[PDB]
Length: 128
Ligand SMILES: [Zn+2]
Image 1 (cartoon, rainbow, N blue to C red):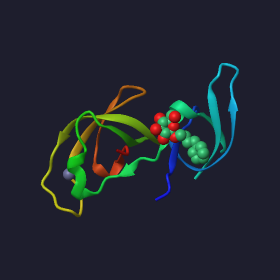
Image 2: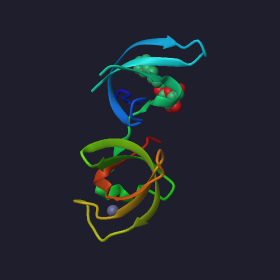
Image 3: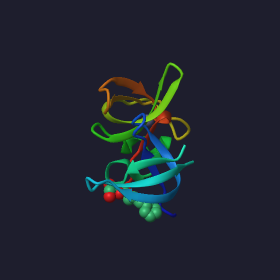
């Protein structure tokens, strides 16, 4: 029930689970950064690059994912595999039960603006 966090690396713009927070600093420009240890230690901007951890979606609740939603998406390309922000553009709804969702979510990645068709098993929702 404790709050848990993910942080966005300024190295590759992808999100990583935070194990703990070590210290902080203020840049001369006024920006506040925290030093995080990941579940390697990095400085990350508090305002833009630390948030409550994204949440897996169970097959029985795939209806809660809607066009326009911000999702954390598993983006696998070549031998690179990053968790990146995307927005759901389109949903092809499938016939399925509680065991496995077969709906297809077309996502558009925020950073490079590319699109990919993903299953529920590669996307996580934001809290609230
Ligand atoms: Zn579904």
